[PDB]
Image (spheres, coloured by chain):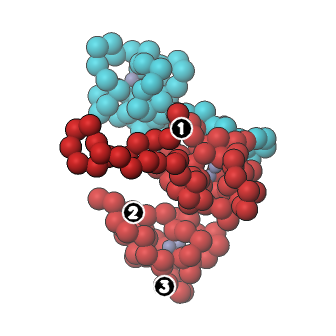
Chain colours: A cyan, B red
Amino acid sequence: HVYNYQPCDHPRQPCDSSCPCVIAQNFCEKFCQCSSECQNRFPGCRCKAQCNTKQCPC
Amino acid sequence: HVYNYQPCDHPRQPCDSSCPCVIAQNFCEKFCQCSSECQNRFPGCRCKAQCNTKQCPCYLAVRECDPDLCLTCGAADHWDSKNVSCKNCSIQRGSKKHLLLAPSDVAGWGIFIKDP
Ligand SMILES: [Zn+2]
Ligand SMILES: [Zn+2]
Ligand SMILES: [Zn+2]
Ligand SMILES: [Zn+2]
Ligand SMILES: [Zn+2]
Ligand SMILES: [Zn+2]
Ligand SMILES: [Zn+2]
Ligand SMILES: [Zn+2]
Ligand SMILES: [Zn+2]
Ligand SMILES: [Zn+2]
Ligand SMILES: [Zn+2]
C-alpha cells in the first residue's frame, strides 16, 4: 500500500485525516507546508552511528 | 486501550494475531518466551545519549529504555553509579528528586521540591 510522497499544502487545516500525507499513510517531511511540529512529521533519529540496525527508527 | 503486559508463552506458534502481546497491542519484551527475532519484540534504541527527545523510539513510544536492549544510550552502563547518560531511564533506576512534606498552601498536606 506504499504511495508516493507528495508534500502537503493545506493551510489553516491540521495534518490529520485530511492531509494527503496522512491519507497516503506517509510521514510528513521537511518539504511539507505543515507546521514544524506536525503530528505526522517523521522525527529524526539520534543514533550514535551506523543506523543500520533495527534499533534506528529511520 | 492500554493493557497490562503479560509475557507470551505460546511455543510452536508465531507471535501473530494469537499471542497475548499481539492481541493486547503490546510489544513483546525480553520476558516473552517467543523467539529472539519476534516481529512484535520492541527493538533497543541506539540513541547517543539523553533519549528524551521524540526521536528516540523508546521515548517516542512512551517507554523507558530497557537496560538489556538499549546499550548505547547508557541505560545499561553505570548501573551502580548515578547521572546516567540516558534520561528515559529514571523510573526504572529510581533516581527521584528530593521531595519535602509541609502543609499545603491550598489544602491539607503538600509535597515541596528541595532543589530546582
Ligand atoms: Zn499535511
Ligand atoms: Zn505532509
Ligand atoms: Zn504535516
Ligand atoms: Zn536517521
Ligand atoms: Zn539512526
Ligand atoms: Zn507471544
Ligand atoms: Zn510476548
Ligand atoms: Zn513475541
Ligand atoms: Zn533512545
Ligand atoms: Zn532505549
Ligand atoms: Zn535511553
Please state the chain letter of the residue tagged with numbered disc 3 in the rendered image. B
Image position of A47 with respect to B15: above or below = above
**Residue at numbered disc 2:** B25
Disc 1/disc 2 C-alpha distance (Å): 39 Å
Residue located at (48% from left, 79% from top): B8
**Residue at numbered disc 1:** B115
Disc 2/disc 3 C-alpha distance (Å): 16 Å
Q: Tell me the SS state at disc 1.
A: loop
**Residue at numbered disc 3:** B10
Q: Tell me the SS state at disc 3.
A: loop
The quarter of the picture where the C terminus of chain A appears is top right
Viewer-side residue, B107 vs B97: B107
Disc 3/disc 1 C-alpha distance (Å): 49 Å
Question: In the rendered structure, which disc, 2 or 3, sits on the residue that comes first in sequence?
Answer: 3
Q: Amino acid at mark 2?
A: Gln
Q: Are marks 3 and 1 on the same chain?
A: yes
Please provide percent x and percent y for residue A45. 64, 37
> Mark 1 or mark 2: which is in front?
1
Q: Amino acid at mark 3?
A: His
Q: Is residue A54 visible?
A: no
Q: Amino acid at mark 1?
A: Asp
Question: In the rendered structure, which disc, 3 or 1, sits on the residue that comes first in sequence?
Answer: 3
The quarter of the picture where the N terminus of chain A appears is top left
Please state the chain letter of the residue tagged with numbered disc 1 in the rendered image. B
Instruction: Point out the residue furthest to the bottom here.
Output: B11
Q: Is residue A39 left or right of residue B52?
A: left
Please provide percent x and percent y for residue B109. 28, 49
CB at disc 3 and ligand 6 closer than 8 Å: yes
Viewer-side residue, A24 vs B1: B1
Please state the chain letter of the residue tagged with numbered disc 2 in the rendered image. B
